[PDB]
Image 1 (spheres, protein in one colour):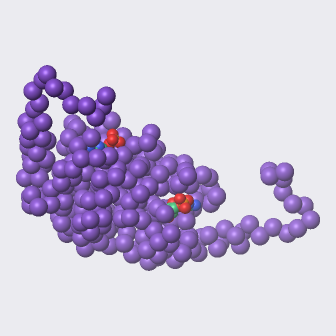
Image 2 (image 1 turned 90 degrees about the vertical axis):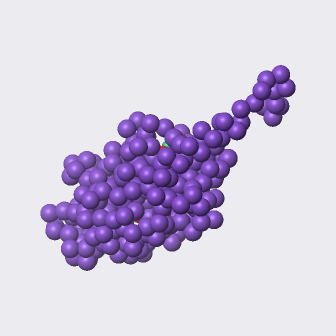
Image 3 (image 1 turned 90 degrees about the horizontal axis):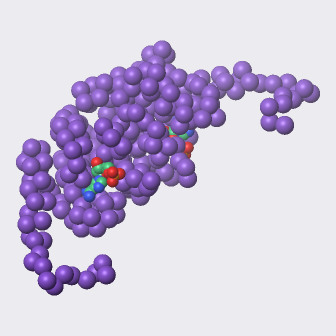
Length: 130
Length: 130
Ligand SMILES: Nc1ncnc2c1ncn2[C@@H]1O[C@H](COP(=O)(O)O)[C@@H](O)[C@H]1O
Ligand SMILES: Nc1ncnc2c1ncn2[C@@H]1O[C@H](COP(=O)(O)O)[C@@H](O)[C@H]1O
């Protein structure tokens, strides 16, 4: 196996579908473990007169992550929902998890180009229908 | 096969060796045809009092291209030695030849980042020992 651990980064756009079945086949053909990441991305002040729905908001993010994770057969131990700047957190989890190929979509300043610039491992940029 | 035609771009540096055996294995594992490209890169005035060795110069470039092409079993019909700007010519041959994955090394303004920005196909950036 040329690569043993692929991290797929998904932004939950319409575009993801292309990369999902492609990455599923790639991982199989080269014999790599898949992990999955989605980054959650008076501005520090919290509204006092309205009810918050942060738990419903997060659950929606979890369900989209799980739709894809289930399709790819990725154990929930290797699915990542993190908050932060996409480029930073994608590279952080890649390094933390011993990933050797990061897969990102590409249509700035873009996420693909930023991950390329800082990645300590190989990067696959799947050209998306922008 | 997720990809049917991989174009490997080589700059003839010490760094190429990493990408060559990696790309050889990748192409085999995913079942893709390999092509290979190296770009040749009073400034328009030609010296009159010295003998030129442009043919020896080109032959050296051909031998380095052929060392790699022979290793990868690439038919000389699919090896490319072109003059121009690397990013432009790499994308030009990719498009001309119906390539679906371009492989480049990555350590600006870099070639990897430029090919990413203009590529109409997927791009693999192999992280080099800079
Ligand atoms: N919040 C995010 N979580 C995970 N991946 C992302 C995120 N935003 C962007 N990406 C990656 O970057 C690609 C294109 O994003 P962008 O350049 O931000 O439009 C997406 O297909 C993902 O691969
Ligand atoms: N003259 C060239 N011909 C083919 N590929 C090149 C050339 N220059 C740069 N590259 C590609 O870009 C990578 C890094 O180049 P650079 O960013 O120019 O240092 C190399 O490993 C090649 O993949």
